[PDB]
Length: 175
Length: 18
Ligand SMILES: *CCC(=O)N1CN(C(=O)CC*)CN(C(=O)CC*)C1
Image 1 (tube, rainbow over the protein chains, first blue to last red):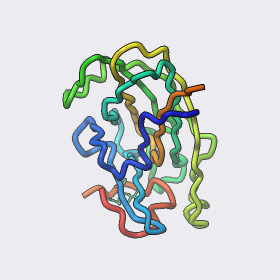
Image 2: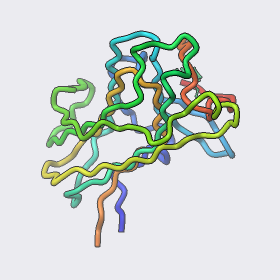
Image 3: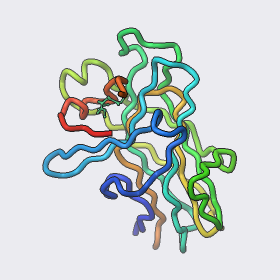
């Protein structure tokens, strides 16, 4: 019933998402756990101010899809949990999309993106949870459409949160 | 260099690369 267009957790870290700026900002992290590779897109520049960190997906061919469903699983760390810890810290990030008939390739083009929503965690990671070695995984879902162009990008803007994306699943529904 | 803080407890498991 759900036809998967993009699946970050399963994609072995090979999608070539684009980050702006450079390599300061969002960072692709890899480890192996339970003899299964594991990917997190992470950023935590909570100390220095004026953070504007963008992450853009590969281009997704829409095909039959007219309404898409974007499921995210992420962690967000408590702004008071930083020994030191700045007044530039935030606990949300922004989700955007862009439709086009054309690949952008490598010029990022934030100006063509439309804001879907502010994404806020139900479960904030606190210093206690590091002690228990247990993960508070937020699950949030948004919907966009109708889509009418050949393809689309998702993008993520961080403005100074300590965020990890574990899962980004994009699908449409066929009945 | 990236000396930034640990995003979540998954980071306690060694071998992470960036
Ligand atoms: C700020 C993110 C970062 O680069 N580091 C913190 N950290 C983690 O968040 C692991 C989950 C450990 N680091 C690395 O793995 C650097 C590649 C440093």
